[PDB]
Image (cartoon, rainbow over all chains, first blue to last red; front, side, top):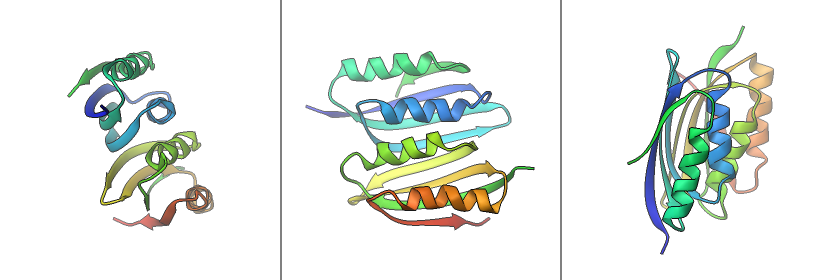
Length: 77
Length: 79
């Protein structure tokens, strides 16, 4: 019942942004499949592919990511 | 001051390893610039670009990653 889901995060690259984002994703109950993260010229972008048990897990993770300082948007791909 | 360095990690895609490696990287005391991680064919590869203090510091981060059971290789990237 687990399925592959994608999430895109965009924000400003300030105050250890990347460490916080990677910390949240790694600690969460999900199986990371792919990460394409770049932080240059003050902007942060990250496309994540993960295996999730259900939609509740996916939306919960997206909600946590939105609370990280500097994040503009978190959208499902 | 800090300079840009690259690190490549290759390991087994089992037992929560991708999450484990991402966690180790997040706990690093450095400025992460790029992460390209992909899990496929039973393994995962991860190219990381970070701004680091000096070579001694870089070596300590690579040693931390190499000590994670399940990691096959950790090498410094050039270019």
